[PDB]
Image (cartoon, helix red, strand yellow):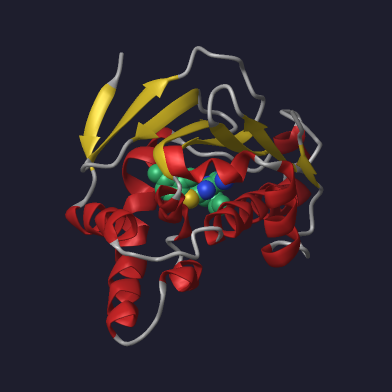
């Protein structure tokens, strides 16, 4: 069963701005997603100190970057805390409302899109390079879910019967036709070195 939801109007507006604004420095999307993965890993690590059983779903804390030219996808995988159904449907978007308002005010005052992460809404920068984003996620004590959106004001959530992932999040970027440079090994390596060189978890760049 696939459920369809409307984004909050403010989030739809943010996504439209990201898609419509002329802005060449698109590569910053990767730093934003890696940053989110790092935060998710920090969270499960912290929680595990008081409840060690939270790592029964996997002790390894890391990030994988997986390009696939045949599917035209770049996947950012982490073994962090994951997300609940409520996270996906309501709670992350609700929190994102304040950051969105502040971000759009800052842009009018002279800020640029690269600063999106300073407002806590960096996830949506995925739409700089992706025509569709699929998020597969598994949180302890909740089921595995697939969230998906091609923007246009709506997203879907379903229980995922695909390959079980243990715990964490996979952000699958279905790249725009003119953004296939982000499938190239040399390009991803360059971006990770430029913007994500001090992340406190292993980042493995898979090759094709
Ligand atoms: C980190 C932190 C913990 C919070 C949950 N969470 C966990 N792991 C990730 N890799 C996340 N990326 C986001 S941004 C985001 C915002 C909205 C939607 C719908 C999806 C995502 C992935 N949120 C994430």
Q: Residue at horizontal 62%, vertical 17%?
A: 164
The N terminus sits in image quarter: top left
Can residue 176 be seen here? The reply is no
| Residue toward you, 139 or 73 | 73
Q: Is residue 40 left or right of residue 13?
A: right
In this view, the residue farthest toward the bottom is 109
Q: Is residue 120 left or right of residue 207?
A: left
Can residue 125 be seen here? The reply is yes
Q: Residue at horizontal 46%, vertical 36%?
A: 84
Query: Residue 137: where, in percent of width, then height?
Result: 53, 32
Query: Residue 139: where, in percent of width, then height?
Result: 56, 34
How many numbered discs sit on the rendered protein? 0
The C terminus sits in image quarter: top right
| Residue toward you, 37 or 142 | 37
Query: Residue 177: where, in percent of width, then height?
Result: 43, 37
In this view, the residue farthest toward the front is 178
Q: Residue at horizontal 46%, vertical 53%?
A: 123
Query: Residue 66: where, in percent of width, then height?
Result: 67, 34
Is 138 drawn above or below residue 10 in the view shown? above
| Residue toward you, 206 or 135 | 206
Is 119 drawn above or below residue 121 in the view shown? below
Residue 38 found in image quarter: bottom right
Is 74 drawn above or below residue 192 in the view shown? above
Q: Is residue 113 left or right of residue 180?
A: left
Is 61 drawn above or below residue 34 in the view shown? above
């Amino acid at each position: 069963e696939v459920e369809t939801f409307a984004f909050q109007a403010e989030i739809a507006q943010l996504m439209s701005l990201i898609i419509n604004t002329f802005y060449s420095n698109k590569e910053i999307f990767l730093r934003e997603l890696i940053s989110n993965s790092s935060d998710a890993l920090d969270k499960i690590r912290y929680e595990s100190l008081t409840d060690p059983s939270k790592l029964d779903s996997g002790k390894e804390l890391h990030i994988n970057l997986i390009p696939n030219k045949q599917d035209r996808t770049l996947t950012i995988v982490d073994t962090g805390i994951g997300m609940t159904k409520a996270d996906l449907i309501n709670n992350l978007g609700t929190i994102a409302k304040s950051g969105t308002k502040a971000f759009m005010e800052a842009l009018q005052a002279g800020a640029d899109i690269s600063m999106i992460g300073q407002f806590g809404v960096g996830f949506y920068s995925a739409y700089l390079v992706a025509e569709k984003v699929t998020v597969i996620t598994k949180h302890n004590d909740d089921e595995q879910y697939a969230w998906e959106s091609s923007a246009g004001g709506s997203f879907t959530v379903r229980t995922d019967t695909g390959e079980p992932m243990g715990r964490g999040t996979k952000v699958i970027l279905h790249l725009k036709e003119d953004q296939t440079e982000y499938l190239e090994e040399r390009r991803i390596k360059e971006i990770v070195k430029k913007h994500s060189q001090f992340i406190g978890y292993p980042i493995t760049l898979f090759v094709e």
